[PDB]
Image (cartoon, grey):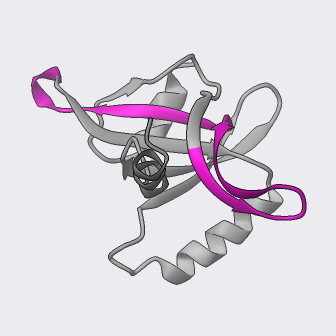
């Protein structure tokens, strides 16, 4: 519902406006740099397992800061929690926030990264190397 948004902004000061639907994911077309068993390369894929929330300034201005909450597996969910707890104290590590929110009869785990930007650096490099 709406309380999901009230959990996402968690404890800081947001002023958060949804960036899509209600409480589900949002498709985007973003440049990835991927290598595994099947696909390999630097190409524009279409990412769809995140929820985006854009931060509102005072004066109800829209500021360049997005809360990106990803919802994915449970087994992966802790591994990332452990490694974050290890690297927590670095200055360059985007502040994470791990929780579990129930939708239907499931407390599905979410991992929210805070105060990130619209475009990553892969997007800059792609846009400047494949220029049309």
Q: Which secondary structure is most common in the magenta stretch?
A: strand
Residue 75, relative to residue 48: is it above or below?
below
Residue lying at the far front of the rendered structure:
132
Q: Image quadrant of residue 10?
A: top left
Q: Position of residue 102 (x, y in %)?
A: 71, 34
- Which contiguous range is marked in magenta? 31-60
Q: Image quadrant of residue 76?
A: bottom right
> Left of 9 or right of it: where is 20?
right
Which of 85 and 54 lies nearest the eye of the viewer? 54
Residue at x 62% of width, y 77% of height: 83
Q: Position of residue 86 (x, y in %)?
A: 55, 83
Residue 87, relative to residue 43: is it above or below?
below
Residue lying at the far right of the rendered structure:
37
Q: Quadrant of the C terminus?
A: top left
Residue at x 48% of width, y 39% of height: 8
Marks counted in the figure total 0
Residue at x 62% of width, y 45% of height: 70
Which of 67 and 48 lies nearest the eye of the viewer? 48
Residue 129, relative to residue 5: is it above or below?
below
Q: Quadrant of the N terminus?
A: top right
Q: Position of residue 97 (x, y in %)?
A: 50, 56
Q: Image quadrant of residue 80?
A: bottom right
Reply yes or no: does residue 49 show up in magenta. yes
Residue at x 44% of width, y 52% of height: 120
Q: Position of residue 98 (x, y in %)?
A: 58, 55
Reply yes or no: does residue 82 show up in magenta. no
């Amino acid at each position: 519902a709406q309380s999901f948004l009230n959990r996402v902004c968690g404890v800081s000061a947001a002023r958060l406006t949804p960036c899509g639907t209600g409480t589900s994911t949002d498709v985007v077309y973003r440049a990835f740099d991927i290598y595994n068993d099947k696909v390999a390369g630097f190409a524009k894929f279409l990412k769809t397992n995140c929820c985006r929330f854009q931060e509102k300034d005072e004066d109800d201005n829209l500021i360049d800061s997005y809360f990106v909450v990803k919802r994915h597996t449970f087994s992966n969910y802790q591994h990332e929690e452990t490694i974050y707890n290890l690297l927590k104290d670095c200055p360059a590590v985007a502040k994470h926030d791990f929780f579990k929110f129930r939708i239907d009869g499931d407390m599905v785990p979410h991992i929210s990264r805070q105060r990130l930007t619209k475009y990553t650096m892969a997007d800059l490099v792609y846009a400047l190397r494949h220029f049309d």
